[PDB]
Image 1: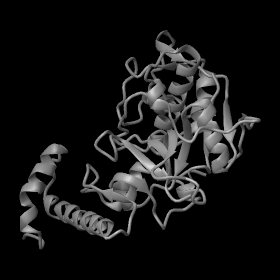
Image 2 (image 1 turned 90 degrees about the vertical axis):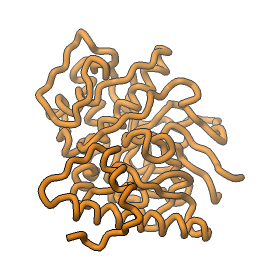
Image 3 (image 1 turned 90 degrees about the horizontal axis):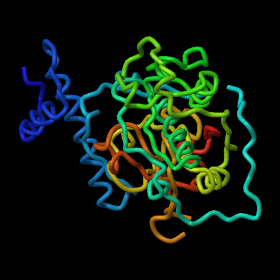
Length: 314
């Protein structure tokens, strides 16, 4: 029987399923639609509250609309471990610009999509290494997350069950290279290692860990390039984020669960209320602002953005 559904959403539901290539099993469509309508109501309430001045950002339905919290746990996976990188050397007699955006200088590849695999650690790492290779050579090449997923087990990563950016940077050093995305395309599943040195386009000399301070993170973003970070993304407000400065009162500066890439920072209004980090995600361009999110900056390390920050040296 029809589990108390909103008749006015039927067409949208039919269209959403097609857009997202859903083909549901026996007796699956009903409870899935119920998940979707509950998320729709949650999004609409939040956005109405936004109209009433209660939030700094809006939400929108996306490809996560039918997912159970348990499936969402498959895509997340949390981050802790010794800090083994080289020491970040604070820039001396230096004030960083008021805004930075490395996309404007060619350091950033297009937004990618991790799919139904807990591999954001690999996307964060490739983004940071893409940035440094570009800094060093002036050439931007998208790098293979699949290469990291399949091959960096020895370094401590766990494929689609999670991993750490510094472990990925370590693998690249140990391995003597990393293949391009084109040569070693993304499958969103862990498979046997197929690294081929012929197709290596990147290398690293180790990595640098940034102190757990947003001021240090700002100096790093200003002087280095894109920075790998982990955040508490484990809230529906982030899952369905659409536009604006993300601020979630329940966000933890610990309990990190999702790796992303800081590509810059800025200030939406003047200069303590409305500063933001510009963050590249790996949930596709449909999510957020073309795949990006502005995360609250200088608000007591909101969502832990500065708690696990690093970059590779090339």
